[PDB]
Amino acid sequence: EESYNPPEEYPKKYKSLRVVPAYSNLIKEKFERCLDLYLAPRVRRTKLNIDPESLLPKLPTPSELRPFPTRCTNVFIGHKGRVRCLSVHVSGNWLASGGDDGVLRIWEVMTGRCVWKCSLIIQSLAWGPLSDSPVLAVAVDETVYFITPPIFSDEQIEASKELFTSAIWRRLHGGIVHATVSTPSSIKSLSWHRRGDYLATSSPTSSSQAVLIHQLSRGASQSPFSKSKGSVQAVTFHPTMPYLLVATQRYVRIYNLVKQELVKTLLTGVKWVSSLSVHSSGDHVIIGSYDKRLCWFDLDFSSKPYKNLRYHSRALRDVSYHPSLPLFCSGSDDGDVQVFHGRVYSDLLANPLIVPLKILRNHKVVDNVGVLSTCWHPKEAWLFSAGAGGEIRMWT
Amino acid sequence: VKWPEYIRLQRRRKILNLRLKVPPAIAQFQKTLDKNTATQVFKLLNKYRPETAAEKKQRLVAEAEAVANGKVSKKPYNVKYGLNHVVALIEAKKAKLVLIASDVDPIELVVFLPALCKKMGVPYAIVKNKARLGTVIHQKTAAVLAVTEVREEDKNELASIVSAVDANFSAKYDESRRKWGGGIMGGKTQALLAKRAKAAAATVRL
Amino acid sequence: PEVLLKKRKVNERTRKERVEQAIAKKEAQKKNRKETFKRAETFINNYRQRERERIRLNRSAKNKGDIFVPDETKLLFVIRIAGVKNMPPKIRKVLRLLRLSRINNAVFVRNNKAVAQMLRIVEPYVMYGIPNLHSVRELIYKRGFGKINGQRIALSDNALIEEALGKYDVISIEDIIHEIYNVGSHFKEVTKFLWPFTLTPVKHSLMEKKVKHFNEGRKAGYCGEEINELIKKQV
Amino acid sequence: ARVKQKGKAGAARIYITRNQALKKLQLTLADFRRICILKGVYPREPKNKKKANKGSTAPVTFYYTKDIQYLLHEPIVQKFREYKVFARKLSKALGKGELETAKRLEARKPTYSLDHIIKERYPTFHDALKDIDDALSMLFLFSTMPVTDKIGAATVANCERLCAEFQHYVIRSNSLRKAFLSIKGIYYQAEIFGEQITWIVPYKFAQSVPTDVDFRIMHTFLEFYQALMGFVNFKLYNTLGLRYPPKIDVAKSESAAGLAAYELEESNTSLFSNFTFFLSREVPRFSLEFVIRAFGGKVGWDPILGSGSPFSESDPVITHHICDRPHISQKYEGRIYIQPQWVYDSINKGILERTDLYACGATLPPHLSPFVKVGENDYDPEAEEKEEKEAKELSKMMMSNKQRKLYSKLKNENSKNENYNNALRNRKRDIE
RNA sequence: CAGAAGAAUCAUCGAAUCUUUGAACGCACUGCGCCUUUGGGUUCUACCAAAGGCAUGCCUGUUUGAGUGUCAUU
RNA sequence: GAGUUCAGCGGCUGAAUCCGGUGCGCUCUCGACGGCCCUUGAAAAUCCAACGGAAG
RNA sequence: GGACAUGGGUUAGUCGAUCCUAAGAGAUAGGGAAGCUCCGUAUGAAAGUUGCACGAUUUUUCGUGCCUAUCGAAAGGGAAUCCGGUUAAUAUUCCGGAACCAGAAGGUGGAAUCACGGCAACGUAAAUGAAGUUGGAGACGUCGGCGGGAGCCCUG
């Protein structure tokens, strides 16, 4: 429908048929048709019978399953640098955060106050599993401090003391220092045992002694591996029976310390592994990777990841699963956080139902770094997100 | 470089016929009629080509139809060809102009023709390639052609061609055809042969 | 059944590179074939031809101031078939006046005494006859070129004709055809606008390509109605 | 058993390259292409090009080995070799100065008939009628081009005859359905034996050859189509009972009578049946005569457009006088003066159109292409967000091959065109 | 002997069949190939089978070539 | 679940088929050396890799 | 009776041959010889099974570029199978169970837009490579002692 006077678009408009010229390209188009007839290869297909691609998607039904961490309403500010790591207490009322500034800030979740402003770089920080012993292990370079803030009840400080009262051990605005542990390498990730008697420290720089196990009952440290192969990126403890999970650069390894043996080596198939999270049931693992990929591992499915997810535009930094609610989060340097719902069914036939729930946005990105760490609330579907600008977003 | 055997034979025969001493009866065929006169020769010869096999049958069937319905001509004029026929014409002193091909393969087929043509008093010329003569007579090759009679229109043309051959082929060469041919050597060949000759003559006489 | 025509396996990059090197070879050969030799016969042959023309021109002019001037028509088609090196100046000018400055040039002429005497002067070089409606139509419709601002422009559209000839009520190719075939008031202006056609002989047969001095057997003189066949072999 | 050598079967054995096809047939590229034009042969790309190329990776065109083996026993190939022999005998005849024998050789020049090529390419007439449109497009394109040293005068004459015969059949059988006018030319759409035929006829103008197209390729396509059209026209004329070929009036052709020269002597199709149109000297008679006579309308035309006019200028029987010139000095009465677009709009819509709107000097209603069908939403010239995003970013999140990606082109291009031509009506209304 | 009922272990003989070899001829001496065409099967770009082909010297012709062999060509 | 050996029954049913220690031991093979060489110690089929950057 | 008579008996994608080459033999090219025949084995051979690639088709008569025998080993080299059971006579072959190799196409999932990490040696589920140019395995004497393992022997 292109002619002398078409209303479709305005080729050229001609006031009359007589003024219409002769198309000088007609022979060229006909010649191109000849060449296409006997030179253009002909491929035969199934003609893609009329089928809108909207039939390919299945039904996630988010309106039913919607523990929505809706838009953030509480913003915590005051940190002058990137919040490298943050953690929430077992009670869920205290959120301790830290970063390269070396300033440790404890925030009250319900009010948003920064009551504990004592500063005391911060690699990571993790609370103890015992409520009566709220000891926070904070890693600074090669030193880890077991700090028990006086904000808690007085008796809890004494309860945390008796837990302990390779790596060398040593025993201020309320600077209640209890135990300082120094390691040859700069520890990257920290993990706590279920009973609080064991501390796992992982460092990527070291090869022989990348991971160290610290027992508070004997007050000593040791290397769980006689011969460690490959760099170690993160470490954690199984939340159901005592396995130790080593997240290397490429693989995720399960080791039983009781037998001192290897259990399963999960092949992420990824250039670089960033961080890992474990479902409370212990048979599902979520892996964040530098390849902008999220890998869901089902220990009862296969060594290979059960599913692969590659929406992030930048490297996936942190992944965390909510301890009670069937939700998990993934924060990357792109400034956007992906919130997914993972429903785990104990039945063999029922495979886990993993569907997206929300894509949180409006987070500042500084020096190609956006979201650094994310934490789940111990009680409800509330998310603490740490940005590179010192902003902590509470996604209720 | 590795030439094929037949290509090597071809080029060696070319050089060998040059280095050797060619007798005067065989060396006179190295000196052919010039390019201008040969063009004028073949202009006259192409007005007397023998009629083609189709054109002859075309004429004969034309006369056959006339008698088939119901029912004196002129003597045909053309060029005379064929070695035995032409030699018989020269000895009969009937040929006016004999044109000998310069590369008849067994050369002795035509080696006596320049002498026989000069003995009988016939103007003759040696022209290039056996194929040019063959083309005139609708053949692949003619060892020799001859002209005995031409129409009164072309009597003056033939008298001019005969004079040109006399001036450019017989008056020319002449002494050059009485000399042994060959012995021609390259630019550097004599110097190489002189070194070889003096080396051989020194003590290599066995 | 889903057959798709993929991109051609022609490699357009190397194709146009091969186009350019072939063109560069043509320019190389064109600048290479220079200064052929001239034998003595060709010089005499020209002189005999020039004397042949001089006698012809004198005999046509002296005591022969007449022309048979074909009738029952007003439009004639004149094609310059042959040319001779170093024409006599009188012949050179008449060909220039009739706009036959190059060989195979064809021009419409109004049949009258003035064009007839000029054609008689230049008779051995031009083949002329009476075009019909069919010959006039296809010649303009397939080889008509106009004088737009003094360059040779194809008559692809009627807008240019209307722009350059609107004062004489000439708007279309068909209007041009009607004016030419009827010899109207603006016939002189239309012929002025029209470029002379270039009816070069066509060599399609293998025999045509090989034979020398091929000019389709273009005879000279007034060919009458046969020129329609000659145009038909061309357009 | 034996160890099977790698790449001795499968795609490596089924597909053959172009060069290997050349050496197999002992053909040259120009002759291999020419036989590929006449036959139905074309490149075929395999799924695994590297495997089919014996492990190599150079970009190489592929053909079926079975397709090539079918060309080993082609009688046309021996005709290509016979032409090479004849061309050399002609060369020897002329080079030896034998003009008459050259003429005899030219008379007995080896020619080949494309009978079995058409049969083996199109088994049934309806198969030919399907891919007949490309042939008709080319024969009409080359029926108006000037003669070249590449394409002969006989070929041009045959193209005109075959095109005119087909136009005569369509007019006689009233098989024409739609005629559309575009800048490229005139698109005709007819139906024969149920099949649909669509071709293009350009406007007659003194164009120039682009000089970038290879006319050797055009020669073989013209040769193939002319044989195809000849046999198609023979059957169509036999179907109508008309003797084939129709006789040619030499005098009428000499006077440029067009279709009137060929007389078909016997061995909403009536949209304009009760009408006598007249043609002025500013309109495409080669197109208007075709459509009007195809739909029953009688035609008279200006004498300068061609002899054999049944009507004159002064004949009062003229119902309509088509004239695209903006000025008519000798205006008639009862012969209402319209523009050419009136006729073709009537053809497309199958109804009589508004002569007042199409009268001389009036505005021109927009041209409608009958080939364009109404789209799903394209403009014809005549709480939820959370569920939506969840249902839209799960296939790009979870689905394996992400074949849903095709929406990025199917919906995107259609929506952009729909948005443009839907907002166009808003702009034009605002301008009004 | 048994069994069968134009017979016949008949004659004549002009039509046919004629396995592997052998001058022995695709290559070898249980095998190993290539080329053209056709066909099959729980079944098809795979596999299989069938048919017709492929020795050497030379002669006549045909086509395609090679040659710094002999020339012609404004 | 096979085999072997014991018990039975009328094919069937029971059990066991285990834990060691070893040696200039014999046989075979592999690894790491040390000599003597001299004449410094078969070939090919076959498979793999590197340099290279044509093409998209 | 290993005699005679009558019947029965040898089952393989994985074991051998088949494929490769060895010393040598040997047809072909050419040359001898009256001759049955002999010499000769890349030799003054036009020594290429479709030697290979390139091209909008090149005056619809093909141009450009590149690279330039066979036999002879059932002990040498070499893709791949074990266990249990079964016969009057056959078993890595048959039966039952369990594997392996080679080649062939599509399909499904995964991977890169010609992939990353580690100072490095190098690693990984992937990670195109034409012409042309190389490298490695095959593939390499013999003797002595030591170390390792298996089976067998000894024995609680």
Image: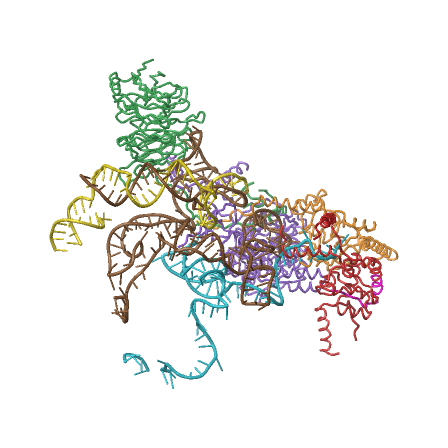
Chain colours: A green, B red, C orange, D purple, E cyan, F yellow, G brown
Name the outermost residue toward the top.
Answer: A172
Query: Can I make out residue B126 in this image?
Result: yes
Q: Residue at x 66, y 64 (%)?
A: D107
Up/down of A67 relative to D75, above or below: above
- Side (left or right) of D297 relative to F28: right
Residue G23 appears at what percent x and percent y? 48, 53
Residue B202 appears at what percent x and percent y? 72, 48
Residue C50 appears at what percent x and percent y? 83, 53
Quadrant housing residue A75: top left
- Side (left or right) of F26 relative to D332: left
Residue E9 appears at what percent x and percent y? 37, 81
Quadrant housing residue D311: bottom right
Relative to the observer, which residue lies in front, A82 or D20?
D20
Q: Which residues are magenta?
A: B143-161
Q: In the image, is residue B146 part of the stretch drawn in magenta?
A: yes
Q: Residue at x 61, y 44 (%)?
A: C17
- For the C terminus of chain A, the quadrant is top left
Query: Can I make out residue C132 in this image?
Result: no
Quadrant housing residue A73: top left
Up/down of D308 relative to A36, above or below: below
Name the outermost residue toward the right.
Answer: C63
Q: Residue at x 36, y 20 (%)?
A: A140
Number of numbered discs present?
0
Relative to the observer, which residue lies in front, B149 or D397?
B149
Q: In the image, is residue A97 part of the stretch drawn in magenta?
A: no
Relative to the observer, which residue lies in front, A82 or G120?
G120
Up/down of D69 relative to F29, above or below: below
Relative to the observer, which residue lies in front, A183 or D86?
A183
